[PDB]
Each structure stands twice: as structure tokens, then as C-alpha cells.
Image: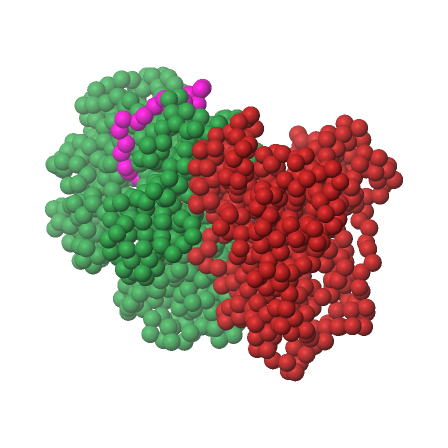
Amino acid sequence: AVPKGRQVDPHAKVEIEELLGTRPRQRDLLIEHLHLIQDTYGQISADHLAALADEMSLAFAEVFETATFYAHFDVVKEGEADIPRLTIRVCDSITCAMFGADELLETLQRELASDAVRVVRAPCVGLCDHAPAVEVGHNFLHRADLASVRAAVEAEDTHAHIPTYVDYDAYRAGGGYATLERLRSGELPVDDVLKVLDDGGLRGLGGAGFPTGRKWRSVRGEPGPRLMAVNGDEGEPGTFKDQLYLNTDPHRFLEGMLIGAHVVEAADVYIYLRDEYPISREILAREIAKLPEGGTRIHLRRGAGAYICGEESSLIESLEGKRGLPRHKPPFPFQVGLFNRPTLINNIETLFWVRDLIERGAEWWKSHGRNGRVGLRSYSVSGRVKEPGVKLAPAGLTIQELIDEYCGGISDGHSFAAYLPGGASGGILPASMNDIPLDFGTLEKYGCFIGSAAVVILSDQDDVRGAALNLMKFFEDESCGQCTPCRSGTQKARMLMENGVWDTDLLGELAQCMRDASICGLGQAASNPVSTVIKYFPDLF
Amino acid sequence: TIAFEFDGQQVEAQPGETIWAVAKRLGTHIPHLCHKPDPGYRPDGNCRACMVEIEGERVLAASCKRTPAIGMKVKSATERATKARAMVLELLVADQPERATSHDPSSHFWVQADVLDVTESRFPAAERWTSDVSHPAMSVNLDACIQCNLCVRACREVQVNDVIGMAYRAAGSKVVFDFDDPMGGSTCVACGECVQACPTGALMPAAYLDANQTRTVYPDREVKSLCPYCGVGCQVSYKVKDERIVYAEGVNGPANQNRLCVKGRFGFDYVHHPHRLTVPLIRLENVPKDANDQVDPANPWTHFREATWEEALDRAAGGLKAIRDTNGRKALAGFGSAKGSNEEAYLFQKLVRLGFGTNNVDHCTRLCHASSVAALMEGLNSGAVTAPFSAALDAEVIVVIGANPTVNHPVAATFLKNAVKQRGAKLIIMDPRRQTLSRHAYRHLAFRPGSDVAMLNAMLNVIVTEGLYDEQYIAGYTENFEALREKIVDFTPEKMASVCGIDAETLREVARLYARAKSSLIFWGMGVSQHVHGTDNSRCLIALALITGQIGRPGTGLHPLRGQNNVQGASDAGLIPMVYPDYQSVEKDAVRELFEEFWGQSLDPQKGLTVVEIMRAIHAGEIRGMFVEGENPAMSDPDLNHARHALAMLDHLVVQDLFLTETAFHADVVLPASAFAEKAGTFTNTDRRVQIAQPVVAPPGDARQDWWIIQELARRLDLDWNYGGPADIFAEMAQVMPSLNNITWERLEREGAVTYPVDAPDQPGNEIIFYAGFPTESGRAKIVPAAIVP
Ligand SMILES: Nc1nc2c(c(=O)[nH]1)N[C@H]1C(S)=C(S)[C@@H](COP(=O)(O)OP(=O)(O)OC[C@H]3O[C@@H](n4cnc5c(=O)[nH]c(N)nc54)[C@H](O)[C@@H]3O)O[C@H]1N2
Ligand SMILES: Nc1nc2c(c(=O)[nH]1)N[C@H]1C(S)=C(S)[C@@H](COP(=O)(O)OP(=O)(O)OC[C@H]3O[C@@H](n4cnc5c(=O)[nH]c(N)nc54)[C@H](O)[C@@H]3O)O[C@H]1N2
Ligand SMILES: Cc1cc2nc3c(=O)[nH]c(=O)nc-3n(C[C@H](O)[C@H](O)[C@H](O)COP(=O)(O)O)c2cc1C
Ligand code: SF4
Ligand code: SF4
Ligand code: SF4
Ligand code: SF4
Ligand code: FES
Ligand code: FES
Ligand SMILES: [W+6]
């Protein structure tokens, strides 16, 4: 019998005792204590995991299982190598790949890499329009090159650079929470807010399209003390819209968040923005502390890789301080939320627009719309476009229109060959099908969807099959590995495509299995690039 | 009930039944890898082998985890579902090592794959983790792992040992133990629950594999019996390979939920020990019976000599006969064993009562829990637990004062952990030293050793002065509630905090929580009992349970943890020198006459001497001649000139042990006994359940059954006993034991176990006793205060 195990070192106990101070030692804050240890010390030493488990009355298995799921926590045991102080991350994703990310990754992985710096790949940092994107110790470099990264590293320009944004007083000078103040006081009934929200037809902008008013009403119907969470994960490779609104007009989002909390009576709300957004984190921390006291207490939570944590059940489980594994859906997350209490989760995009509907009317929202579709959408456009960035355009906008009316053209020396609507989650489409309106319910008949309005333009200078391989590798790395079809199917599909010619029939069968028997939406869409490139690019096999 | 449609035909589903369970009931079972249809395993739908098609849904559903709702239409034979299941199996097979030299090539996974006709895979295999063999008893080879997660449920939900987890993401997600260590140095307790929960050979016992980690041994025979280590009555299924026990699996007993500890999984090798007595031994006349002599177990012929089963047996039964007929009937005594069957214990005490004609019957295992049983009998007229340890699943507050079940009754501790982790149960560990259960404890009242009566009296004073007691229960079911009320005033938390180790506010909180709880069980062991003057420790515990009313209803009672195979059934058999079988007083004239007429011989009126009394009387020479069965008094109590010297002064010692133990060093005749593995009979556990044991192997050499030796000694003592086996002995003793009234050998063979206070043949017994009064003459219990007189 060998039940001894590993003895918590006394030195590691005092360090976590002083480190935690008076913070609550409840499992719900496990991820946050992991962040605290990872930040105070560039790694999470095994003795530190043991000390944290002792302080939080957990098992070593529990803390290790939680802390090795996120790709930004560096567990280091007695035999592992010490992580260097500076960690520069090179995005390896479709757009940064178009702009020489892999070549750049190799370049600075052999030139400025050393024992004092670590160069690793990253899925995506929402900086696609400024590709290639590289992070240097919380400082993300736009259109990174060898010289720029070298200057950043040698100058110690590691910390994030906070931009100029409308502060709390500036927001007061205009809107200034007047709509919220008219809600916290009985001047406009909550029924009117829901009525206008439903009439406008605003739909969830995180990549589902579910009406916001319906979510709010359904959660309001559920009894008991309700809760609310905000999805700032925005992990889709082609999506950067949310970061733009966080770092420009945070208080519009905060007003929407407070309106949603009041409409639901949620005593408190949680924000789950990425750790790839130091700018947004600092902005919210500054402005979260300037709102008036009372109302609903608002918590700002931080992520760690784990693209899957953007899934609502996964986000719930991550907020619970455990692995961001999604949940089965006999119980919906609005019925049984994070603490088993009904909660609504909304993207920071949809919270950004509620104020305008309440103050400017539903007719304003329904006045826009290019094709038969209605509404207003923020498009994240990157790649082979003359002007890449977030485009606030009407709904039902065909990609040809979105390119030659908002992007200023395609490029010099490039031709429009293929595009992917909705990002990696959606499938690649040929440029010959440019007459397809882009909206929530107009892209399914082609096996695609536009979740976050992430649009990446493929030219004739880039191979569609390489793009599909990149997307498959992204899904393979990002799957939480809970169910079989996703965990194993992503790996098998990636393996099948490292060959010169892959088996179309086998890939189709595996894609059908993945799409039919996967637990969450990550695996139900992981095979979309493969099937789409097979179907709409017959002349590539 | 839900009247839904499955595979085109309407069916009915019991409440809480999943679609998979309904399908299995109707016979149309479907593949399952992550789902383990055994008690205690929560269906997790992460294998997607159980996929079915239910109308109205955009995707397939895991009948593993999904329950049928009214109007639901399910189809599992459709092309969609069959293809999805086959693709899942194909992916996993592509990940599998092999099916010729693999780990458990007949595993559950391979059976399910054969069901789906998935022999090979079209998808490339992937390199996996290396085999790990650090732990001696069981080898993990994750290269076969399916990530079905069953092992984490087994370690963290069923046993709640918390030594397993899936820490990585994606395909890299692997099974770890604690910080991904090789297990051989982790906190693993080797209970084997994960090994019994793996659907592949990724987790196997190390005795089924070889150097190459391929399955080698397939046990030809498997026999189900009990575990002779704990008093928890943990049922086992022993695996026999070439007339040897090579592995043990837990079965669905009523005390264990298919779960064992390390001692049930392994440790069976004691039966096949090389140094196991096989032939009777007689002490040769040349060798003197030295006080400090040590017989070599490897060389038992330095002090003893070979002899047939009629020479040694005659010597044993003749020395005692001569002693009784010359020195007197009061010069003999016998020590039974709480390790043998109830039929052996009854037969042994009957021999010591008839052939020796006295009451000098006492098994050394009763010294521990002696005080607790004394107090429980004084207050309640019954020494048995009031509730099963499975009652913790219904109790709101659990008290584990003075016990360490996680080490000594691991399955009971697992049930306590399940109560905590699945119900709103608050367990309080009232132990001076920190305990593994402390991490799951609402409070841990670490108090100075010996300062237990003080703090329990403080809790009683809190309950009394605060009016927490329910006057309704006292007035109608108890006596003497006013006597303590006079003296409880003196003991108060403010004063008792100093002498104790708990602050007054903590004592107040614990007492209030215990009193106001709807249900509240108390568990205790040797910590309070073996402590000098352990009757007071028990007395105040009974007072707490009694004034508060926490007794006689589900989730409530007093359950001292008996740490021996069948000490409870040994006492029920009459191995006590102060009472007959079934706790019938030996001094009562009516009881004496009942046995005198039934046993057909005059019986000794005066109560027999206790084990310590016998040991100290050996020194005075009042008692000369013994018969020790399944006990080692030579190394039980302090043995310098009180226990070892006592045995050497015996005129004639007979011992019936499995090994040439220390107590057998001074034995004139050694009787090779059969172990629990190679014996039949019945055993009673701490839970008060009577279970039947079965032989798995044969005794080494010509070693005989214990009851056979006892009967032979009786026959040579003129008793003329004729029993054909344990069944006849059980019937005879059931004819005289009110406890075993409506239970028979035929009924005990079926159903595995029967809690003996039963009313009808088909009734399940009375797990909770004292529900409608107490067996006391007045029909109500007594509240006895505890006296502190240092
Ligand atoms: N696996 C296993 N099972 C066994 C045994 C074994 O060695 N291993 N041995 C057997 C033994 S002979 C008997 S029959 C039982 C033992 O049953 P147990 O209850 O386990 O007896 P102990 O282990 O000696 O102590 C139990 C707890 O009492 C606490 N304690 C110590 N001092 C005090 C005190 O002054 N007051 C109080 N209230 N508590 C105190 C101790 O810290 C300890 O945690 O289990 C038996 N079964
Ligand atoms: N040094 C020491 N002394 C102790 C204790 C201790 O743990 N250590 N424990 C103390 C208290 S708490 C209790 S545990 C006791 C110790 O507990 P004991 O029961 O007195 O010691 P064991 O060796 O466990 O008892 C088993 C004995 O009976 C035999 N035996 C086992 N099974 C069978 C069987 O199926 N049939 C037959 N015929 N014989 C069998 C074994 O060979 C051995 O001689 O005394 C106490 N004294
Ligand atoms: C794998 C996966 C990842 C997702 N990640 C995000 C995300 O990072 N941000 C987001 O707003 N929605 C994300 N979604 C969409 C979810 O619907 C989201 O968690 C939530 O529903 C947003 O609600 P809303 O549309 O009402 O704002 C993701 C969905 C899936 C399947
Ligand atoms: S589909 Fe992928 S991410 Fe979703 S639960 Fe299954 S393995 Fe995890
Ligand atoms: S043998 Fe028991 S303690 Fe060890 S890993 Fe398996 S379930 Fe956990
Ligand atoms: S070790 Fe066995 S039980 Fe555990 S996840 Fe792997 S296949 Fe399942
Ligand atoms: S808990 Fe007790 S009865 Fe059950 S296997 Fe372990 S030692 Fe044997
Ligand atoms: S930052 Fe590189 S693809 Fe988004
Ligand atoms: S049958 Fe559902 S995962 Fe095993
Ligand atoms: W004992």
C-alpha cells in the first residue's frame, strides 16, 4: 500500500498564505488564485499547487486537473524546466498565417529566443486586422516583425499600452446611465424595456442568434435568486469586434450589463473577458470602480486560453473554478446556471446595443438592413483586404458588398479566391459564391454559419486546403477533450490532412460522426472547414 | 411512469430510469463504454457510444445520461445512430494497442467493439503514454485508455478518495493520480475501485499481466464470500487460478456497494502462506515449556513432533478430561475467536459449557468495545448498533468521535464521504489528531486526549440549558432525565472549555447543530471505548442521542464501529462468560433451566470468569488447562509476566490456530485450523447483518475445519455431538436464539445477508431498532449521567 502521496512543503504554505491574504478560499476562485500565482511567479510550481489545495481544502488531483486545462497556466514539477520570465506568443492562425506568422515564429524562435525568453505559438489574440499579431509580456505588437519584436523585448516594452477612451465622466456628460437610472427608479417599467428589445429583434451576437428579449424574459420567469454572466471570451480566430468596444466605449457595455441585471434582478453579475485582452481588463478595472455604489455588485473574472470557455456551459464551469468542460443540455444554462441558479449569459457586443434600442427606439434598429435581412451588425474583417478592421454595417450584406463598399477593395497584386464567414467555426467558401447574404439564418443551407461575423478573405496567393488544415489544427488544440467524436475526430482529421492527398470519403464519414455525436458546438462545427472545402472546391483533389 | 416509444413500440419507464436502462430492461441493449450500470456510478455521457436518435432533436442523444419524457420517440437501430456508435468505436480502436497481446483482450471495450463489428480502424493510430508499473498490486497502461472517465468517478465520487483526474485538454487529456505521479508514490489507497471501473485493460491488477503487460491468467473459478478483515461485512468475489486466490473483486453486498478496500482487493495471500500449519503437532516431552522460548515458524519441529489426527486429537481431548476430573470443572477455560463463523463460536462456547461444565468462555477481542457495550446495555438493554452505517446517507449531522473509519472501515468511511458530498450532511470529527476525513468535515473538534467526557457534558449542558431537548421524547421513552439535570448544571462550556480543547462558542455551535438536526448519527470506535473508564464516554453519548431524540428513526442512532470480522456474531453466539447465547443471563433461573433442558445437562449457575480474570487466575493456580481457538493472547495484552508467563504455567494448552503463532509456542497440542477462505458458516458485521461465507479453496495439507475439531474434542469429552456441517450448528443455535428467529440457512444462502431482527420471511429486516420503544423491562431507556472523578 502506498497512500503517502506528496507532502505539502511548509515553505509553499506560507507563500500562499501571504499571497492569498484575506481573499475568499472557495473553489469558485480557484482559477483566480491560479492567475495570482502565475502572475506573482512566472510559473505555478507543484509545491504552490499543493499549498493552494491545502489552503482551499481540495485534493492535489483537483487543482492539477483544473490548472492544466487552460494553456496559460504553466505547471512545473521538480523535473520540469523553469519557465523564463518573458513569454512572447506568436499567433498561428488563418490570418497571421497569411501574413507569415509561422515563418516569423521560426525566425524569432531561433534569433531572440533564449533562457530568459520563451517563444510559443498562440491560437489567436483578436488582432487579426493588424496581422501578424505577436504578444510580448502583455504587450501585443501590431504587424509584428523581427525588428519590432526585438525592440520590444530589449526595451522591456512588455506591459500593455492603455488607449484613450471615454471615461466615466465623459459618459456622464452624454448618456450617463440615464436609462439605467430611469430603471432603478419607477419611471419606465421593465416591461417597456423588454417590449422594445423584443420588437427591435436584437439577437445574440456571440454566435448563436438567439433573441436577447426572449432570453431576458425566460430567465426572469425562472424563480429564485437569479444571476448573470458576461461572455468576453471571444476566442474565434477571426473575431475582434468585442475588444474594439471594450477599449473605446466601456460604459455603454456596462450600462447594458446593468440594465440586463436589473431586468433579471440578478444581485450580482460576472464578466469573463479573456487574458489575451490586458487592455480591456485594465479599462474595466478602472471604470468598474467609478460607477455609483449600490444596485448589483459586478465581478470581473479573467480567463486563461481555453477557447472552449467561450461556450456558455464551459464559461459557467470556468466561473465555478473548475475545468471549462461544457455541460449536457437536458437542463439549459438559463434554468440551471453557474451555481445551479438561473442565469443569462450575453456577449459584450449585445450588451453594447441595448441602450441604443431603449433610447433611440426599435424602428431605428429595424431601419437598417441591406438585403431582406434587418438589423445592424459589426463585421470583423481581416486578411486580403486593403482596409481591415471592424465594420459596423447592416445585416444581409453580401461579402462582395462588404469588400467593395467598406474594405476599400481587396488588395494590390491579389485576387478574391475564397472567404470564410463566421471565422474558423464556419466553413471556407469560394469567391464565386459571393452573392450569399450574410446573416444569422441565411448561411446554413451551404453548411456554413456567421457566428461572430468573423470574415477572413482568401486570395489566389493562399491555398484553401492549408487554411482548412490550420483550422483543423486549431480545433484539435482547442477541444476540451471530453467526448470522443471531438477529442479523437479532430486529431484524426488533422492526421488525414498531413498527407499529400487525403481520403474524402473517410473525412466525410468522420465529419458526420463529429457533427452528429459531439457534445457541444465546438465539435459540431470543427469539421465545417473540411466538409466545405471538399464540397465547394472539387478541383483541389 | 413515462409511457414513451422506443424502437417503434410503446414502453414504460420507471422514475429515474434512463433510456439506456429501459432499453436494457426490454432486452434491446446498446453499446456503452463510459456508462457503468452499477450502483454509485453517475452516468456521464462522454463516450458517445450510447448515442440514440430521438425525434425533434437536431443531433443524437446519449441514452447514457438522458431520461425518457412523455411522448418521446427513440430509435437506436437507425443508420444515423448505428454509424455514430460505430465511428466512436472505430476511433477508439484506432487508438487501441492490440487485441492479441493487449491488456485484458476480453475487456468490456472489446466486447462492445465486437457487438458493433468494429474489428479494425481506418484512422491512423497515435503515439500514447508509456506503461506504468510502479504500484505493486495494480498496473496502469494508459496506452489503452479511452478517457471514459469511469476511474475518476470511482476515485472521486464512489470512494471519494480523490486520487484521480483528467488534467489535460483535448486528446492530450490523460488520467493522472495527483500531480501526474506514477501512483506508486501517490495518495492511492489501492482499493481497486478504478481497476474494477475500467472498461479497457488500461487499469488492471498486476497479477493478471506479465513483463510485456499482456493478459496471462484467466481465473478458472470464482467464489463469492465475505472479507475477514473488517467488521463492515464487505462481500467479495475471489478469483481462483490453479487452486490459488489471485485476485478479489467486490460484489453487491448490503454493507459494501460493490466496493472494497486494499484488504479486500488483496491480502488474500495469507491463506496460501508457506508457513501455514498442515499437520497436528504434539509437544515432545524432552523440551520444557519455557517462559520466553520462541519457536521458529520455519522449523516447527524443534519443540513439536508429527502425529496423526487421532493421536494429537486424543492427547488434546484427554488432557482436558483428566484436568476436569482431577482438579475440578473450575480449572478449565476456553478462548473463542471473533474470526470464525457464528457456528464455530456457538459450538465452542457450547463445548466449554458442557464438557468443562462451567461458564469460563471469553474471547479476547471483546476487551475492546467492552465499555461501550457495557454502557449501551446499562442504558438501552442492548449492545448492538441502533442504525446501519448506510444510515449516514439520510442523516443531516454525522459524528465520528473517537474513530478513524477511513483507515479501519474504509467502505463505511466512503459512505460517510458520499453522504457529505451528495447530501447536505455535516460530519464532525471529534478526534484529538487530524484525520483524512477532516478535509470533508464541517468542523473538527480536536480536544486534549482524555478530555472527551468534559466536552460531551458541555454539549449536554448546552442542550439542556438552552431548551434544545424535546420534552416529548423524554416523557414517554426514557427514565432518569431529572437526575443528570441536577449535575449537568456544573459542567458548562465556559468552564469545560479550559479542561477541554474546544472554545465555548464552538461547543455551543456543535451542540445546537446536533440537537436541531432532523437526523443525526454518531459513530465511535476504540478512541472512546478503549480509553480507561470508557463507559462514561459512551454514557454521555447515549445521553446526547436520547434526550435529543435522535434514535429509532431513519438516519438516527448510535453505531459503535466493530473492528473485527464477527465480534458481534461471536457475542451473539454466547462467547461471553456472564451470559448465554443471544444475551440471556446465566444467573437467571429460567434462562438456566431453558438451556439445561435444551442442552440436556446440568449447567454451572455462577457466572464465568472474564478473560482478564482467567489470565490473573492462572497465576494463582486456580485455573490450569485451556483451549484457545483463533486467538493470540500471548501477544494481545501487556505480556512480560502477566500474559506470556501465564500461558507457560498451564498444565495443558490446546491451540487451534492457522499458523504456529506465539500462543501456540506453549501449546502442548497444536490443531491445524482452516482459514476463512477455506471454511463455510455465517458471520455478523458491525451493521448487524448476518452473512453466509463459502469456501473458495481447500485447507493446506490435511488441515480440518474448526467446527470439526471442536466436535471431535466434544466427542472425546463424552458429549456425543453429531453435526453434518455449519448448517446443522446454525439450525441448532437458531432454535435457541431469539435474535435469529425468522431467519434460516436456506433463506440466508439466498439474498446473501439478513439483518437478523426480522419479522417475516420476506421482510428485509430491521436496520433501525428502538423505533417503538426499548427492550428494557419498563419499555423505556435510562439516561445515566457520567461521573468525572480524576
Ligand atoms: N485496516 C485495519 N482495520 C482494523 C485494525 C487495523 O490495524 N487496521 N485494527 C482493529 C483494532 S484491534 C480495533 S478492533 C479497531 C480499532 O478501531 P479505531 O476506532 O480505529 O481505534 P484507533 O485506531 O486506535 O483510534 C481511533 C481514533 O481515536 C482517536 N483517539 C485517540 N485518543 C483518543 C481519545 O483519548 N479520545 C477520543 N474520543 N478519541 C481518541 C484517535 O486519534 C483515532 O483517530 O479496528 C480494527 N480493524
Ligand atoms: N501488539 C498488539 N497487541 C494487540 C493489538 C495489536 O494491534 N497489536 N490489538 C489489541 C486489541 S484492539 C485487539 S485487535 C487484539 C488483537 O487482535 P487479535 O485477534 O487477538 O490478533 P489477530 O492475529 O488479528 O487474531 C487472529 C488470530 O486468530 C487466527 N485465525 C485467523 N483466522 C482464523 C480462522 O478463520 N480460523 C482459525 N481457527 N483461526 C484463525 C490467526 O492465525 C491469529 O492467531 O488484542 C490487543 N493486543
Ligand atoms: C465553442 C464555442 C465557443 C464560443 N465562444 C464564445 C465567445 O467567446 N464569446 C461569445 O460571445 N459567444 C461565444 N459562443 C456563443 C455562445 O452562445 C455564447 O457562450 C453565449 O451564448 C453568448 O450569448 P449571446 O449571443 O446572447 O450574447 C461560443 C459558442 C461555442 C459553441
Ligand atoms: S465537442 Fe470537443 S470541446 Fe465540446 S465537449 Fe466534446 S471534446 Fe469538449
Ligand atoms: S485504487 Fe482506489 S484510491 Fe487508488 S486510484 Fe483507484 S479508486 Fe483511487
Ligand atoms: S483508465 Fe480506464 S476507466 Fe479510466 S478513463 Fe481510461 S479507459 Fe476509462
Ligand atoms: S472495508 Fe473491511 S470488509 Fe470491506 S474490503 Fe476493506 S477490510 Fe474487507
Ligand atoms: S490574431 Fe492572429 S489570427 Fe487573430
Ligand atoms: S454509454 Fe454513455 S458514455 Fe458510456
Ligand atoms: W480489537
Residue lying at the far bottom of the rendered structure: A187
Q: Position of residue A259 (x, y in %)?
A: 64, 70
Residue at 39% across / 62% down in the picture? Answer: B556
Residue at 23% across / 22% down in the picture? Answer: B702
Q: Which residues are magenta?
A: B209-234
Q: How many discs mark residues in the rendered view?
A: 0
Indicate how the structure is coloured in the image.
Answer: by chain
Q: Position of residue B310 (x, y in %)?
A: 18, 23
Figure chain in green: B
Figure chain in red: A
Magenta residue check for B228? yes
Q: Is residue B412 above or below residue A502?
A: below
Q: Is residue B445 above or below residue A225?
A: above
Q: Nearer the viewer, residue A109 or B500?
A: A109
Q: Position of residue A243 (x, y in %)?
A: 71, 54
Q: Position of residue B102 (x, y in %)?
A: 41, 24
Magenta residue check for B177? no
Q: Nearer the viewer, residue B758 or B448?
A: B758
Q: Main secondary structure of the magenta part?
A: loop
**In the rendered image, is residue B95 in sight?**
no
Q: Nearer the viewer, residue A330 or B411?
A: A330
Q: Specify whether B572 is left or right of B515.
A: left
Q: Specify whether A353 is left or right of A329.
A: right
Residue at 59% across / 39% down in the picture? Answer: A471
**In the rendered image, is residue B76 in sight?**
yes
Residue at 74% across / 50% down in the picture? Answer: A408
